[PDB]
Image 1 (cartoon, rainbow, N blue to C red):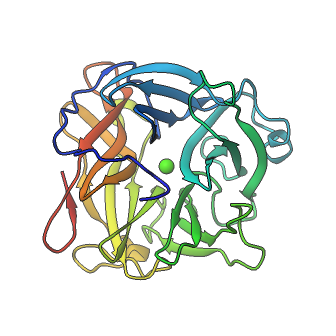
Image 2: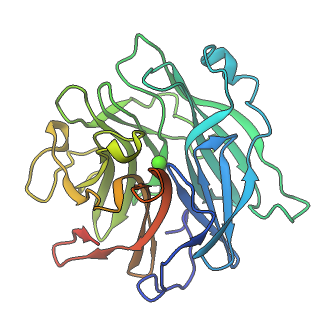
Image 3: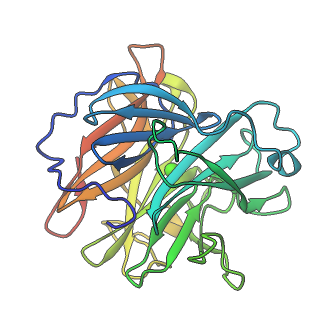
Length: 312
Ligand SMILES: [Ca+2]
């Protein structure tokens, strides 16, 4: 897709036996030239790079320190770890969204940073702080974290986000500011319809006429005790209603489980989906049962059946 370009690569053909610096949580990927980049949760937003998409190495971070303005939104924030970044390339500009918050609370704000290139070796490399995108406070019934931008088939950009509380949110963005359009309304598109409303990390992609909403169910961040799972639903309209393979509404716990983990990789979640031709990859993290539950990067080929539903 134009905003997540990967060129001509047959994802199904390469061997995704990842090696190197694989500690990652809430990842997203971008490719520029022949280099691959992973952005994920960590101090100032952690960055990893690879020459082939298989062998990874730490590259640094986006922000040297917590941008000043963030402190006004989340006063309690006493460390520099930013979460769940999202990235897309539009009009020659890289838009990187990130979350500023504290665990289990909804006093949060999603920020935006831009750059013309992802290669730090380029003298033009520079992440610019573009300020607040959308926020939430204790009085709101949603949480402003876990952003994801997608463009509908009409070329209009939309921002989905959310974690617990009322669930997954969706709002229309302005192409110029890449921030919520002044007259845009906040919509709720997915919820476990249960408490705790364990649903978060939305990621939307368009595929052969349908918008697929990928989300993570249950509990992350508990190492080998994690119960994280990747679920998916779809809709012909980006605003919903999203439903799973069984036809269950995603506003009532609906969602087809794509992966619930195994004996080695526990609690897989917070995914991203990217295409190249008809091929695609599922990107996420999982807690390594053999390595003290360490969050680990996973990149695997993602197939699609006749009805249009994805599978690993
Ligand atoms: Ca995400």
